[PDB]
Length: 180
Image (tube, rainbow, N blue to C red; front, side, top):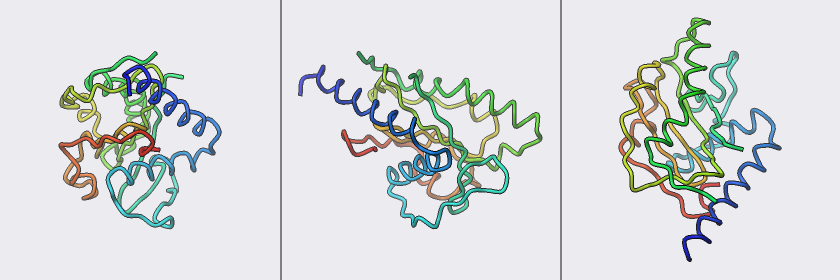
């Protein structure tokens, strides 16, 4: 496939994900993100494994994980370096870190999970992910990303679920249509 038509395919894919999210119910949307992420990592689950906690945060409980789910959206595509892609999480992560600090919430029990879907950008998978130092400093137990094109565990502390720790140091790249 010529590059232009491939990038078009990835744009239509991004559009499809947005169309779904904009019409989904809140907890269902968050659970859906968790399912897509677990599928990316080939982590088995049954539907009964997902639960909502008494208090938010987090959003979705799964086998010891406390998934705090957030969306990184933007609405002819450009390839964005992994560093710049990772930086797209910063505004929301800063706001959460602040809000939770003000409430006396233990950041260290939360496994952050970003659903990243940009119509204007596609990751440049030839570029390396830099250490997530700002996000490490915010005190989360773990931070992961998933989108139609890829999934990656950015970091996970020793106390994080083993399935997170097992997937450090790697990115999962989806063929078109496989991520969603």
